[PDB]
Amino acid sequence: ATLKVIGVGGGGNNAVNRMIDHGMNNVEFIAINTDGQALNLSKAESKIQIGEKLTRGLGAGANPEIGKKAAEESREQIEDAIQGADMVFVTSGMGGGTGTGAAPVVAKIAKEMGALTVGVVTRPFSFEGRKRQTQAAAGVEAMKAAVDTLIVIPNDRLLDIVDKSTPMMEAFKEADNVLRQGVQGISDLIAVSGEVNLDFADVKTIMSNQGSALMGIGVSSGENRAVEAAKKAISSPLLETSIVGAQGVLMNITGGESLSLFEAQEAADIVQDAADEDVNMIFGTVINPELQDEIVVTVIATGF
Ligand SMILES: Nc1nc2c(ncn2[C@@H]2O[C@H](COP(=O)(O)OP(=O)(O)O)[C@@H](O)[C@H]2O)c(=O)[nH]1
Ligand SMILES: NC(=O)c1c(F)ccc(OCc2nc3cc(Cl)cnc3s2)c1F
Ligand SMILES: [Ca+2]
C-alpha cells in the first residue's frame, strides 16, 4: 500500500517540509504550489508547479478561483505524480488563493484515481479577518465534498495551547503532528502483522466515503496506563471534530508482553463511551516485547 503526502499552497508545503525534516520513511512527498519561489525551496522530492500560465510563478493573491483554475490547468501533471497511490494525504491551509482553490481539486483527482483520500486542513486565525475565514469555509466545504475523510485544524486552537512567549513556529509543529502521527500510524499498521491484526482494508472500511474524521494517539505507562493512553488518543485541544458522536472506530493497542485483556477492555470502553454512540469498532492489538512498560493507543474515528 502506497501512501503519498501532498501539501498544496504555502502552509501545506511548509507542513511537507517539516514532516520531511522529521524523517518520514516509506512515504512519498509531493509539493504543489503556484508560487515557484517557495516550491524551489521545497525538500519534497516530487515538485509540481501549478498555474504557471495563470500566475507567472507567483501565488494566487488570496483569490481561490486562481488556485482552483491553476490546478485544473495542470490536471495531467497532478495525475502523474499521484499515480500508483493507494492512499493520499492532502494537506493545506484554507483561506489563501492556492490551497482553498487547488487543494479540493487535488483531492478530487486523487479519489478519481481510486486512492483513499484524506485531507488535513487548517482554518485561519480569527485575527486574519472575517473575509479570509469565509473563503476558508468555502474551501473546507469543497474539501469535504472531494475527500473520503476530513480533519479540520482551526489555527485558533493553537492559542489554547501556548503561553504568551511560545514561538509561532513551535505552535505550528504542534499542528504538524496531527497529520504526521496519522500517516506514521497508518504506516505501522500496514507494515506489521499484529496478534489481532488490522490492515489497509480495515483502514479503507473506516475512512472511505465518510465525512469528518478524528485521528489520535496516546502514550502512557504506570498504573492507569490503558485508560490514560486512551484518554490522550481522543483528546482534542487542536481538533474541530471531537470524538463525541462517532459511529465507527478503528482502534489499536500496542504494548509489551504484560498487556492484559482487562486493560484493553478499559481502553476500548473509554472510547466507545466518549463517542457516546453505538460505535461499530474494528479492534486490533500489537505485542511489541521491546515496549516493556509503555502502552500506545491509537484511534481513527469517523461516522458522525
Ligand atoms: N497552522 C499553519 N497554518 C498556516 C501555515 N502557513 C499558512 N497557514 C494558514 O493558511 C492560510 C493560507 O495561507 P497559505 O497556505 O500560505 O496561502 P496559499 O499558499 O495561497 O494557500 C493562512 O491564512 C494561514 O492561516 C503554517 O505553517 N501552519
Ligand atoms: N493490529 C495491527 O495490525 C496493528 C499493528 F501491527 C501496528 C500498529 C497498529 O496501529 C498503528 C496506528 N497508529 C495510529 C495513529 C493515529 Cl494518529 C491513528 N491511527 C493509528 S493506527 C495496528 F493496528
Ligand atoms: Ca498489519
Image (cartoon, rainbow, N blue to C red):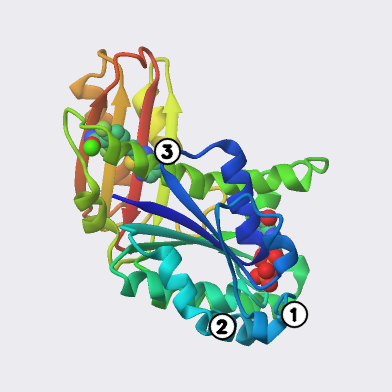
Pointer 3 residue Cβ closer than 8 Å to ligand 2? yes
Comparing marks 3 and 2, which lies closer to the viewer? 2
Asked whether mark 1 and ligand 1 are closer than 8 Å, the reply comes as: yes
Residue 267 is at least partly visible in this image: no
Residue of label 1: 61
Instruction: Tell me which image quadrant ligand 3 sits in.
Output: top left
The vertical placement of 119 against 68, above or below, is above
Disc nearer the start of the sequence (1/2): 1
At label 2, the amino acid type is Lys
Reading the image, the residue beneath label 3 is 217
What amino acid type is highlighted by mark number 1? Gly
Sequence-wise, which precedes: disc 3 or disc 2? 2
The first of marks 3 and 1 along the sequence is 1
Q: Secondary structure at mark 1?
A: loop
Q: Quadrant of residue 268?
A: top left
Please name the residue that numbered disc 2 is placed on.
Answer: 68
Q: Give x and y (percent) for residue 86.
A: 30, 57
Mark 3 to mark 1 CA distance (whole Å)? 37 Å
Q: Residue at x 58, y 52 (%)?
A: 44
Which x, y percent locates residue 110?
A: 38, 69
Residue at disc 3, secondary structure: strand
Q: Is mark 2 within 8 Å of ligand 1?
A: no
CA neighbours of label 1 inside 10 A, class few (<14), some (14 to 19), many (20+): few
| Residue 196 image-quadrant placement | top left
Q: Amino acid at mark 3?
A: Ile
Indicate the position of residue 105 as horizontal and vertical percent values: 47, 78
Which residue corresponds to the image point at 51% horizontal and 84% vertical from the top-left?
72
